[PDB]
Image (cartoon, rainbow, N blue to C red; front, side, top):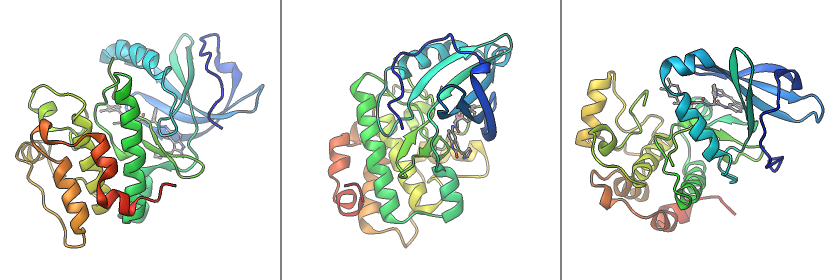
Length: 264
Ligand SMILES: Cc1ccc(C(=O)N[C@@H](C(=O)Nc2ccc3c(c2)/C(=C\c2cnc[nH]2)C(=O)N3)c2ccccc2)c(=O)n1Cc1ccc(F)c(F)c1
């Protein structure tokens, strides 16, 4: 299912694949379902236009991110099989996550129950701990960049790595131009946790400027249905002071998480 091949190579051409239905769209590329002709392996092929990548000044980010990603082997991170190119465009060979994005699940369910939410948060904390363990700090984490495996397991799908768009998930130190460390994504978990339970992120607003101020001020409120344990956890993660966010160990041990996650 996931342990295909570790020898990533660039002798792949478009003629190796039968192309299927469009899976999603982004600014630069379309992602398609695809099947490798020889093996019949189902995967997703994301197609990005080279000229657009260079024009936007992100091609170097892509080379470095691909190189990093090729090293990451983890059940809650989408596995990257390889890449190649022709004259017009650049092709990324990605794991196919059949149950789709958490974003769509949120749109379909309106909000998640504490069980879905705490399972998702455990999976994210595990994945970010693994990423942090190899010097790979993460940028923002969006429900759009969370996929679901055949058993409903979460897969981190965004390239927010290191050796923007909407800010909803960015911590103050990332938006105020301050210094940021691995604690940025702890902020991200609080934002995602809130959105999972509530159905929108804690600082959502009609305009970018309003949102900027709400994040900077940490101006958010809890609806009544949000339980005492979740309020406490979100409040621990959504701290202005990076130094005040917990370690991932502490997150995984939080009594609301331990009492609510469905992860055997
Ligand atoms: C901010 C952001 C968000 C998302 C991406 C991103 O690309 N995810 C890739 C992806 O979806 N894989 C994938 C694999 C198997 C799947 C599915 C999806 C799926 C269903 C589906 C689709 N849609 C809702 N459900 C299904 O059933 N099986 C992807 C790669 C290339 C093109 C499109 C998607 C991302 O890069 N960014 C960063 C970003 C980019 C451009 C900006 F301008 C910006 F500001 C920020």
